[PDB]
Amino acid sequence: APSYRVRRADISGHGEEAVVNAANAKGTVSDGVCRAVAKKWPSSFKGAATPVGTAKMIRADGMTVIHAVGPNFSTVTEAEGDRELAAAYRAVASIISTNNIKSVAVPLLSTGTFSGGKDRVMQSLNHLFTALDATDADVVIYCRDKNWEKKIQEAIDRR
Ligand SMILES: Nc1ncnc2c1ncn2[C@@H]1O[C@H](COP(=O)(O)OP(=O)(O)OC[C@H]2O[C@@H](O)[C@H](O)[C@@H]2O)[C@@H](O)[C@H]1O
């Protein structure tokens, strides 16, 4: 069975075997998780472009980087975004299980730039749990907000 922890820290400082980038479909560097990932593992972005609702893995700079593209909720209906966000997390879970990845640092996809101006912490976290429950990985969820850290910890505990 998988294990879940939350850290309020820069995800670039994670101690896990792999890291999930909250990526865009074009594989460009922009504000958010992506900027921290690009600074720490700059060569991890070579050929990383992948469609919304999918994930693409690379080994670069001594790290396993999983580029997961959540939906931009400004560009899809709520129901379409919900399906695509579930799909991105399942694509992450598949990469974890098929590559025997023991531990992974994961941000909450579609909760920043792609949030469409809405609070989607619980929506994104619930899809993270559902998808990564299919793995036996040690999952560490990364955030920067003290409020988010507490709600994520509350959610982990309820399980
Ligand atoms: N370095 C970081 N470490 C940990 N958490 C972080 C970090 N940077 C941002 N976060 C948090 O991770 C969550 C996801 O943030 P985004 O990176 O904005 O993710 P998303 O909404 O999926 O959009 C990602 C996209 O932003 C675009 O600029 C860019 O193209 C990138 O692909 C947000 O709650 C944010 O507070």
Image (tube, rainbow, N blue to C red):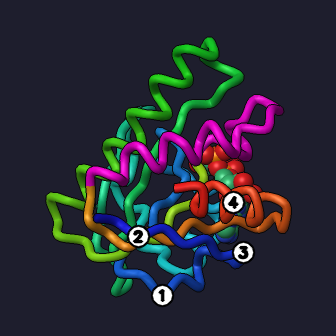
Give the number of the disc on residue 154: 4
Circles 4, 3 touching at the beta carbon (< 8 Å): no
Residue at image point 63% right, 16% down: 78
Which residue is under mark 1? 15
Q: Nearer the viewer, mark 4 or mark 1?
A: 4
**Looking at the image, is mark 4 or mark 2 earlier in the sequence?**
2
Count of numbered circles on the image: 4
The percent coordinates of residue 118 (x first, y second) are 80, 32
Which amino acid type is marked by label 4? Glu
Which amino acid type is marked by label 1? Gly
The percent coordinates of residue 143 (x first, y second) are 69, 65
Q: CA distance from mark 4 to mark 2?
A: 15 Å
Q: CA distance from mark 2 to mark 1?
A: 15 Å
Which residue is under mark 3? 8
- The answer to whether residue 4 is left or right of residue 152 is left
Give the number of the disc on residue 28: none
Image quadrant assignment for residue 111: top right
Range covered by the magenta-colored residues: 109-134
19 and 145: which one is in front?
A: 145
Q: CA distance from mark 2 to mark 3?
A: 17 Å
**Ligand 1: image quarter:** bottom right
